[PDB]
């Protein structure tokens, strides 16, 4: 079905998922000149001290690290958020080349990759229920640029050969996602959507200003994953990003400057 190829990529999605042409689609270009400092935003509270990772999965589109979300452990709050959002998983989007791969752009700049830490609003009880609500999810987006290796990423990079193909999973316990954060928690925020089908308009996006640095070797390893299942023709999992979508009426707010 949907994917990122010429035949089933982002410009095709609207035929199965009409909200693809909706009023709050993601990602977007972040025009840093037009974003407004909002002195009423609070600092983000990223509380990942008790995160419990469980598993890593190649889902055929990306790979995702999944967390135990059956209690309040790893939570995002503050900033533009009302209430408490629980971390359920993180995943990445990346390019076939270092000069593309991110979903959001900054003044049209593309980064090599983008990390998404997905959280759901605990007022809706479960992730699945939250995926249906306008303020159901909060996704923390972090850009990756190629430079110095990110030591906190290497445990993820090293397990990818065990999940090469669609539907493969591996145990992945005791991974600390604090090691994927940049120094600064300065951010942009705007209301948007899932960037993959079903493209539901349920996401408060929080995009950090500071990218993390990863090495060329780290991102090359992402590019060795496969979209296909085992035993099927090999198609490299690369360019699994949706381009920027129309901003429409929306305002992007800055936590800083
Ligand atoms: C490239 C390809 C491979 C296969 C196996 N089926 C298809 S048919 C198809 C499909 F199943 C889809 F789900 C989609 S979509 N709107 O992108 O979700 C599509 F465009 C399609 F063209 N296309
Ligand atoms: C709707 C749904 C349900 C489930 C269980 N996983 C997913 S995986 C996923 C995904 F692939 C994504 F790309 C995103 S994203 N880019 O953060 O909007 C997401 F939130 C996701 F949760 N999506
Ligand atoms: Na659940
Ligand atoms: Zn994503």
Image (cartoon, helix red, strand yellow):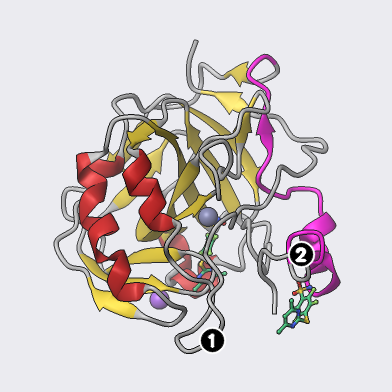
Residue 24 position (above or below residue 171): above
Residue of label 2? 6
Judging by the rendered image, the residue that carries numbered circle 1 is 232
Indicate the position of residue 60 as horizontal and vertical percent values.
Answer: 52, 74
Residue 162, position in %: x, y?
Answer: 28, 74
Q: Residue at x 50, y 10 (%)?
A: 257
Taking 164 as reference, is 243 left or right?
A: right
**x and y percent of residue 235 in the render?**
56, 71
Q: Dot 1, crowdedness within 10 Å: few (<14), some or many (≥20)?
A: few
Q: Is residue 21 magenta?
A: yes
> Ligand 1 within 8 A of label 1's CB?
no
Q: Residue most toward the bottom? A: 231
Which residue is drawn at the image coordinates 32% and 31% (left, top)?
A: 182
Q: Indicate which disc, 1 or 2, sits on the residue closer to the N terminus.
A: 2
What residue span does the magenta drawing correspond to?
9-33
Secondary structure of residue under mark 2: loop
């Amino acid at each position: 079905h949907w994917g990122y190829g010429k035949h089933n990529g982002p410009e095709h999605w609207h035929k199965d998922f009409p909200i693809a042409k909706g009023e709050r689609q993601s990602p977007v270009d972040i025009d840093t000149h037009t974003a407004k400092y909002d002195p009423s935003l609070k600092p983000l509270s990223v509380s990942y001290d008790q995160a419990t990772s469980l598993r890593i999965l190649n889902n055929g589109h990306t790979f995702q690290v999944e967390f135990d979300d059956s209690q309040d452990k790893a939570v995002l709050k503050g900033g533009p958020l009302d209430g408490t959002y629980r971390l359920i998983q993180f995943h990445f989007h990346w390019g076939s080349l270092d000069g593309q791969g991110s979903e959001h752009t900054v003044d049209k700049k593309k980064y090599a990759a983008e990390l998404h830490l997905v959280h759901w609003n605990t007022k809706y009880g479960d992730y699945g229920k939250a995926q249906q609500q306008p303020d159901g999810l909060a996704v923390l987006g972090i850009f990756l640029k190629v430079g110095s290796a990110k030591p906190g990423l290497q445990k993820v990079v090293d397990v990818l050969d065990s999940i090469k193909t669609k539907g493969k999973s591996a145990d992945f316990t005791n991974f600390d996602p604090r090691g994927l954060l940049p120094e600064s928690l300065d951010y942009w925020t705007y209301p948007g959507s899932l960037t993959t089908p079903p493209l539901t308009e349920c996401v408060t996006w929080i995009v950090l200003k500071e990218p993390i640095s990863v090495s060329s070797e780290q991102v090359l390893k992402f590019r060795k994953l496969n979209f296909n299942g085992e035993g099927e023709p090999e198609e490299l999992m690369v360019d699994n990003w949706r381009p920027a979508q129309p901003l429409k009426n929306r305002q992007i707010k800055a936590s800083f400057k």
